[PDB]
Amino acid sequence: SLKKGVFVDDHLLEKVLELNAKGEKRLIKTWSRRSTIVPEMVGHTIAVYNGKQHVPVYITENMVGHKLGEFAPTRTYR
Amino acid sequence: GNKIHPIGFRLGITRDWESRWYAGKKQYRHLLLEDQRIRGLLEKELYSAGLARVDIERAADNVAVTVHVAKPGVVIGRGGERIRVLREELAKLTGKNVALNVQEVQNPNLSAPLVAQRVAEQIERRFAVRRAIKQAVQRVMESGAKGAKVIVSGRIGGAEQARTEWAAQGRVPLHTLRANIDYGFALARTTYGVLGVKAYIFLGEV
Amino acid sequence: ARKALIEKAKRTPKFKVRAYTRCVRCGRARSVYRFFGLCRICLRELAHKGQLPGVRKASW
Amino acid sequence: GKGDRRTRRGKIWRGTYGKYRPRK
Amino acid sequence: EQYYGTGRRKEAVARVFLRPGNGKVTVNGQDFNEYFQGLVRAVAALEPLRAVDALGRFDAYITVRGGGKSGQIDAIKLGIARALVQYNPDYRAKLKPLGFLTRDARVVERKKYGKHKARRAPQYSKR
Amino acid sequence: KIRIKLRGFDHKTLDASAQKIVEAARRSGAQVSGPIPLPTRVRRFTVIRGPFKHKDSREHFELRTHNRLVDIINPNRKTIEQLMTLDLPTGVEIEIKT
Amino acid sequence: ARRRRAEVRQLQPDLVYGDVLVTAFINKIMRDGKKNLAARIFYDACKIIQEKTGQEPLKVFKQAVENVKPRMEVRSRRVGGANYQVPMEVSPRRQQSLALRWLVQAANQRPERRAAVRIAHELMDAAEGKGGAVKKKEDVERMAEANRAYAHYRW
RNA sequence: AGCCCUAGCACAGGUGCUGCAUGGCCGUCGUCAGCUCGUGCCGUGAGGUGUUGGGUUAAGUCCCGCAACGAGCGCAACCCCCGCCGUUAGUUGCCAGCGGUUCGGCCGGGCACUCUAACGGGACUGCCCGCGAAAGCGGGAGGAAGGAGGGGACGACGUCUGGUCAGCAUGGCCCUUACGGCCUGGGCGACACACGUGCUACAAUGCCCACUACAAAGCGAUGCCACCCGGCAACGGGGAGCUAAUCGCAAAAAGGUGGGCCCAGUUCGGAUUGGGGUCUGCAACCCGACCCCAUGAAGCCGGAAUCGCUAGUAAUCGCGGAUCAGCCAUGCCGCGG
Ligand SMILES: [Mg+2]
Ligand SMILES: [Mg+2]
């Protein structure tokens, strides 16, 4: 399950870090569902692609080490 | 849907390979693909010679390439104006230095792989599908063979129901290992679809 | 898609994981032996001709 | 037997090694 | 001084030298009963002697390798017998009636494709 | 003291082509420790006969490397002559050693 | 067995009492092809007929077996209208097998927790003539005899 | 000139439909003892005879008989492996025999033996009894092997309008700013259910732990990894050897011997779930396998039904390989005990 970094995506932090020099966005869309949710970069509601669309996932502290797609489920009535 | 390939079956006695070159577990893949694109260009751009075997040898950057025909000169020119073009084409893709023999079969109606092509040719020139078989067998049986047999698959005469004409003579002991039976397979790209032609010539023994 | 595919399998790719074998003859994704680049089909074929050196029918 | 990764058999069968089947 | 036979039995080969006198039997550098320990049938391997009455008035030195403990057991049995025909022509006329002299032709028959196991085919359900 | 390897697909023409090296090293060399045959390295392939589902009924192909070994204890240039060039191998490999 | 009448696969004699009939028995005891353990068991069982009775094991074995051989049995028979259990005699090869089969089975049905004891007791209790083997012997003999009426077909 | 870039054009491309337009290749009846032809003869003819009959065989195998006499595709035999002996050959065998041995066939010394691998020999109903017209059948001797010694490869005319246009080839038809292409993500892994094929068990002829060469096919130089150290371990360091009958994967496991559990849903059985980690890979949520701590489910040998196998077979126990970064392999193809 890894232990040398958290294999989280370049294009995502670039956008998170440089969003947090004063930034409060929900319109933030992404296809990088395999990137680990990073220590406390919370607040911002990410929009995750499940294969069909982007899901409004508002993020909290207690859901950190989890990868992004655990919240954007990929199939229906399960 | 039974019956082995009769060369495959006999690569023990009674028949040797179209490639007598040794090697090992990282060259073979490539010493092969080459081996093939060689015959790739040869079989396409030398059809008229009428090339039966295309035997090949190797020993690091040399290659024997003994091309068998019975129209041997149609490969050459009238002195060497083509056979020079070819040792040129070969070594252009084969970044190596290519030998290039040429050969004559003293009797081409014993060359199954020709007998096939001949009959195949005829079929495209809307010929007599059944007397072709009748003739070709008699040709091969004429050149002192011990046994002959020819097969066409189907759409015989453009027919909508695919059929199968066959004809034979003398022995063709397809179950004997010491048989020495040449096997020729030819295509036939007619307007209405592809026929397929097989040729079998018996000779051998002890 | 078998054409745009046979080609793309010759390329070098973003990340080497996306590589793979492919019957160089019969352009084929599955059952391609490493010591040949050859689909079990386009293979049983050559083998029978003798175009494959030293390869015999096994029997015991 | 062959299904307990914590028997020795469990590991022969699985093919693996570890505490319950070490590499000699 | 010396005598020989070569016993074989299904991947198992038996180098056997007898010597006169004692009764002890070294096998791959071990006493018989250390190599064949608990293995209830081994006492048979030296049955060829009890056949001729050389009960235990030979020693024997024996290398035996290849495959199996019980196959070895029978392998030896062939040596112990093929050895004494070559220390007496007439050691024959009462080992044939018991046939300690036949090789024993039998061997792991081959795994065939499509079967599970040589002969055992798989399970037909029909509907 | 010469140690030359001989690998092959064709069993009959190692024992052929490299038993010219048990003559042209006996006639102009001297002592010979004969050909020693090393166990074969058999490479089996197993193919389903048809192009489609018939998972039983297959064919078996094996390509077998026959390995042959030669030692000769008189290293002259009396020998490196027919054993420099005078050929009849055509799909062989050789390792030259000392 | 359409063509020939099949040779009775012969057995190596025992490496102890020297009896075919023993190995026969040993073979039946054998499970997954483990003849070793199989043999240990039968011998270790002969030891519990010293410790228990003054008699010689072999004699007990023989005499118990002889006690579990049936003489009659009902072989089934179809006829177009009903099913008929027809009593015929028992050929000595079948006797041999049923007995030895039955012993082992009777024996593995017993309570004691160990191979060599179950064998032993059974062997004793049946040479006395009160085996659970001997049950499924007098039953067969009885089942014939009760169907003594149909005993006039016997093909 | 080439070659490249945009604007055109002729064209490419399509795993888009048709296996009932096809080729090739496979499966099936079935390794069943059959299916035919030439000429003669019988019949107005379709056809028959031959190929039926009697004996015999695994077999249309042979024999005797006969308006038939022969032949071809089959069967058998020619090829591979396994059994017994010889010939040739020594970086695998060895006190087999003697010397040295830090006691590791390691060091000289030697292929005798074992083996490795190439060629040969051997079995033919040839011998004796008995029956028979014959072929051959029942016995016996010799012999490693008897009467097809055991396993393969090998599939007749043809049948199933069998299978496959998605391996490839191919007639035809349909798409051609899209039924072509390229990418990011998702799906092929969904789950009230129902069959197939398996794996693992339900235990004491058993489980557990310790020790204890019986070895008999294969794979390895962008690799097999000996040996050291770190870690309960997966694995991570360093690092030797071997293009490999030399070095490595490699421990075979059932077995043997000791000990332990005492008939308990258990020291049987290891499903489920919690947690912490290892590895491969750009990346392991959906969707990897591995190690360890915990959790321990159903299962006490299975209704009516139904499958496999006749001997080294079945039952049972491990070993390797192919594809492959890794792997969902309990599958497959193989090896021995
Ligand atoms: Mg009439
Ligand atoms: Mg699927």
Image: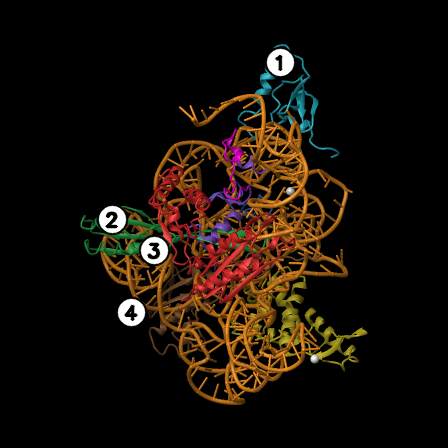
Chain colours: A cyan, B red, C purple, D blue, E brown, F green, G yellow, H orange
Disc 3 and disc 4 on one polypeptide chain: no
Q: Amino acid at mark 1?
A: Leu
State which mark lies toward you, 4 or 2: 2
Instruction: Decide whether the magenta segment is chiefly helix, strand or loop.
Output: loop
Closer mark to the observer between disc 1 and disc 4: 1
Which dot marks residue F85? 2
Which circle, 1 or 2, is nearer the viewer?
2
In magenta segment, residue C18: yes
Q: Chain of mark 2?
A: F
Helix, strand or loop under label 2: loop
- The reply, left or right, for residue B101 in relation to residue A69 is left
Host chain of mark 3 = F
The numbered disc on residue F13 is 3
Ligand 2 within 8 angstroms of badge 4 C-beta: no
Look at the image and say whether residue B73 sits in the magenta stretch.
Answer: no
Residue type marked 4: Glu
How far apart are the two marked residues, 3 and 4, measured between alpha carbons? Answer: 46 Å
Contact? badges 1 and 4 (CB < 8 Å): no
Q: Nearer the viewer, mark 3 or mark 4?
A: 3
Against A67, residue B116 (above or below) is below
Which residue is more in the foreground, H103 or B201?
A: B201
Q: CA distance from mark 1 to mark 4?
A: 99 Å
Residue linked to disc 1: A19
Task: Calculate the distance from the C-alpha at mark 3 to the C-alpha at mark 1.
Answer: 76 Å
Mark 4 neighbour class, 10 Å CA radius: few under 14, some 14 to 19, many 20 or more: few
Q: Amino acid at mark 2?
A: Thr
Q: Which residue is mark 4?
A: E1
Question: x%, y% of residue G92?
Answer: 63, 78
Is label 4 in a helix, a strand or a loop? loop
Type of amino acid at the residue the image marks with label 3: Thr
Distance CA(mark 1)–CA(mark 2): 78 Å
Q: Are marks 1 and 2 on the same chain?
A: no
